[PDB]
Length: 405
Ligand SMILES: NC(=O)C1=CN([C@@H]2O[C@H](COP(=O)(O)OP(=O)(O)OC[C@H]3O[C@@H](n4cnc5c(N)ncnc54)[C@H](O)[C@@H]3O)[C@@H](O)[C@H]2O)C=CC1
Image (tube, rainbow, N blue to C red; front, side, top):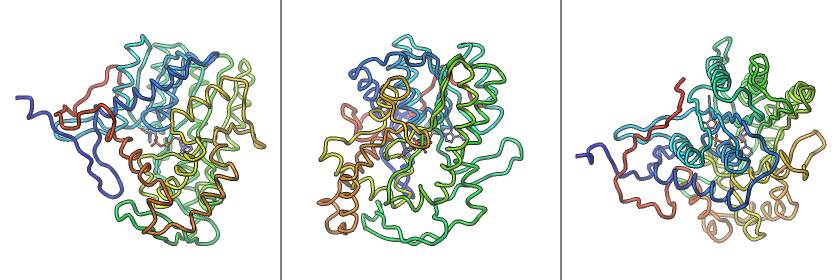
């Protein structure tokens, strides 16, 4: 019988990483984000043909949902995910994208996806072909890539990004989510090679290659728009994201966008912006001990002010207010800001005060570690309402219109 091909999927955590995902729960999570967008209402004057680079999880998935179900856009998505198979659940991003194709088709929306290395020339060429065959051109390009490594499309060199400070070693407090102990560790300052590598991986070169491979193709509409997602944060994380190796990468983004805006604004009044979003739980959060503690504190503080939100709420506002509306939130460098509720002085002062009082004993009285754990499990499709986690499921979920690179 088919029970031999099905299985009961449960959370399995190895190395602060959940190595399983639940297809039914992932589908329920995507539908929850779709339902939020539709309940909030349509978004006027948004793009109608959208390319989302990094479209399977987190903010990129939220952008695909907002564009599709908020602006009514046909969406082409690029991601790097593992399909499921007998006895081996695929990645959450695979099941999320399967659900997106299903729900998009129900609403008569075009949904095609490409699975492969977005840093490579091959994948850029497949994406170009897809646009030529189906859409003609795209109005908006969302760059939402997060990877620890990058294979250079020319030299073949493999760059690995580093999460380290610059100048002086730093003592970072954090929360070990396997042991549930508050703990500190010292990070050494990044070497020059580590900094260049992080710029190469998380900088803006690949975003630039995408736009310049699409422009000479040519598949960008008049008034075309593009934005890249980033995080700046405040003092608690500044040793890494302001001044650290990743801060060096974000400094790269800030200058490469200038070249992109120049090229687009001559092309029908288009526009390009770095968009700064708030911190959220992602698949890799528990692997950096600082973020679980910061997010747990931030969640409690913001919940007490009625300002807590996740990916789909952040990105729905970015579209409605800044990318397509007339409530844009520019900053001195020319970045779009949607993180202002996280950076509110009273929130950060309260997170900082608590940051110095949390111990192993009072974690659940001072932080929303409960909420962090729930949202973390939700990423992989676990703990979702309405899902019968006792039922067998076939982990081999297929995706129509999925180009395998
Ligand atoms: N997580 C956070 O708190 C914040 C993240 N951001 C930014 O948002 C953007 C999205 O990242 P996140 O959503 O955090 O994590 P994420 O892991 O949720 O999403 C990463 C996406 O990139 C895709 N991807 C990774 N390597 C790839 C490759 N080689 N080829 C093709 N696709 C590949 C994945 O399939 C996935 O769709 C990033 O630029 C990040 O810096 C901005 C503010 C806060």
